[PDB]
Length: 270
Ligand SMILES: *C/C=C(C)/C=C/C=C(C)/C=C/C1=C(C)CCCC1(C)C
Ligand code: NA
Image 1: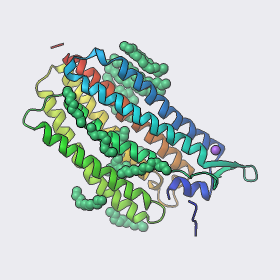
Image 2 (image 1 turned 135 degrees about the vertical axis):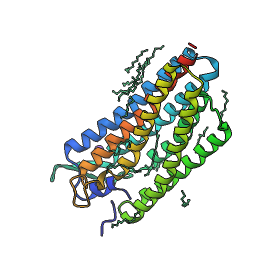
Image 3 (image 1 turned 90 degrees about the vertical axis):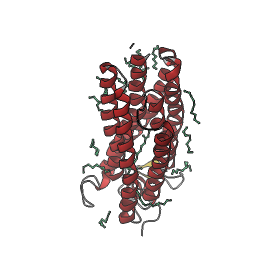
Image 4 (image 1 turned 60 degrees about the vertical axis):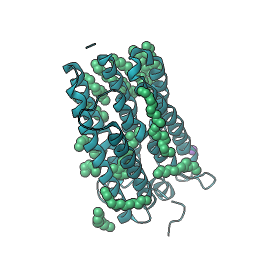
């Protein structure tokens, strides 16, 4: 009965361990992640004057997301290198008992804080038509909170009870679907009052949103996408999961923010 290896990262680290390549690749991608959030923070601060006052709350929410993402992705990166240590005998990296072990806390806290602000910020750039600001905001905030909480409950059972990990994943996915449905309505209403140039940016925001947000549940399932005896049920699934989370983070926070800023500028021409 394995005791030291809470999450799939710790499990692999405690059993098979990590190759020099898997350990170094993961450390570099997590470092890239926090480095891009810091670059983003400076970009959103320095370009805030490029949009009319009425849109600047969006630029502010982008900057605030970047502060929390930078700090918590920095903490996640340090957590990776501190949790696994090289054994000369076998020549791999194993879970270090003298460490605090890999912790999903940093990532899930990041999501809890930033999901509501990413959903909120579009409501300061587009105008609704038949929907109420307060109704859309409340739906986004409730569904967003329940999605991340149900997901967090799931992640605990990942190694101890796979079945529960999936059922909680499914409940989380139900809230996710409601978020996609609301955002699609917001984007369609936002297109009504604006130039074709603005409508085209909103079409690109929808595709970026749909893809980047679906990467999260994809990374959540990554180790189990080739079955329990599968090639992903390994350090390869851990590498893939951390890579996909980093791509999702850069896309859902930084690229999303840039596109909204670009939309605000096109509304700052007609
Ligand atoms: C910058 C961080 C963002 C936008 C985080 C978004 C996270 C999700 C959309 C997560 C959704 C999940 C599911 C739909 C099912 C599995 C568990 C989650 C929480 C990963
Ligand atoms: Na180490």
